[PDB]
Amino acid sequence: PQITLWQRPLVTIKIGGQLKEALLDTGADDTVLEEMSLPGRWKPKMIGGIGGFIKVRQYDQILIEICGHKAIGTVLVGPTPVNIIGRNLLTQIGCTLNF
Amino acid sequence: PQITLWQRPLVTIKIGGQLKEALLDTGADDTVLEEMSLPGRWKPKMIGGIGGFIKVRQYDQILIEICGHKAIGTVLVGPTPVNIIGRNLLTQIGCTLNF
Ligand SMILES: C[C@H]1CC[C@@H](O)[C@H]1NC(=O)[C@H](Cc1ccccc1)C[C@H](O)CN1CCN(C(=O)c2cnc(N3CCN(C)CC3)c(Cl)n2)C[C@H]1C(=O)NC(C)(C)C
């Protein structure tokens, strides 16, 4: 689909049997999601941006269905204000920026 | 042009006769530039990122050329990791997400 930027580009993603809404973020290297339990073991990690850094848990090789498109990748779980889909997963669904 | 997200979507912007590197950020509602001198007065604004809120200086009606596309809009100046081009300026140059 062709998403415009008049409003925030939120899409419905499905992960772990839960349907969540997330932002398609081209400025985000990683994919950060709000606190939830994911199977598998995790690795502690610090990610930052404007406002500073936050501690998250890095779960590898998780499956996320972004608007029907399946994607596999690293997912960081932590105290983020909004679920964000980064470049790692955006590339897998063939997302591009045009202008 | 079409931009894939395998790498960071950095473009060259021209602001105040100076060239700068900037990130095409669809997850950014606003355009936040690094510390520089801009013309006119400024108003205060609180913007929240991943690590929290910060204070920035709001300058209105600033000319900024993004990849040869001129845009006149609101630019915020404050403590940011990199120059960020947000939805406010992306909509002006006609930027969309496709997939
Ligand atoms: C624009 C602001 C105004 C108000 C909101 O609209 C707001 N938007 C945002 O802040 C959104 C989130 C949001 C959305 C809605 C509501 C609230 C928040 C995130 C933003 O789109 C992207 N953001 C760009 C700058 N940036 C970097 O350049 C960067 C890159 N690399 C670094 N590193 C670490 C490793 N090193 C090796 C090399 C340097 C460091 Cl420290 N920093 C951090 C990055 C970010 O946050 N990435 C994630 C993985 C943490 C998500």
Image (cartoon, coloured by chain):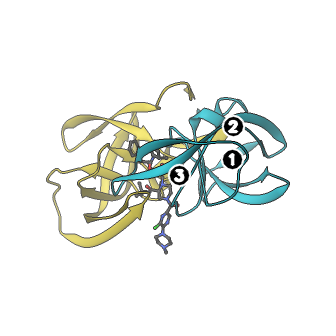
Chain colours: A yellow, B cyan
Front-lying residue, A48 or A92: A48
Q: Which of A87 and A7 lies nearest the eye of the viewer?
A: A7
**Quarter occupied by the C terminus of chain B:** top right
Mark 3: C-beta under 8 Å from nearest atom of ligand 1? yes
For the residues bearing labels 2 and 1, Cβ distance under 8 angstroms: yes
Query: Percent position (x, y) of residue A98?
Result: 69, 37
Residue under label 2: A98
From the image, tell me which residue sits under label 1: B3
Residue B98 visible, this orientation:
no
Q: Is residue B9 left or right of residue A13?
A: right
Picture layout, residue A36 above or below residue A3:
below
Please name the residue that numbered disc 3 is placed on: A27
Q: What element carries label 3?
A: loop
Disc 3/disc 1 C-alpha distance (Å): 13 Å
Residue type at numbered disc 1: Ile
Residue at horizontal 46%, vertical 42%? B45
Mark 3 packing: few (<14 Cα in 10 Å), some, or many (20+)? many
Front residue of A58/B56: it is B56
Amino acid type, label 2: Asn
Is the N terminus of chain B in the top left, top right, bottom left or bottom right quadrant?
top right
- Image vertical order of residue A31 relative to residue B27, above or below: below
Q: Where is residue B89 in the image (x, y as percent from the top left)?
A: 65, 36
- The chain ID associated with circle 3 is A
Name the residue: 59% across, 42% down: B42
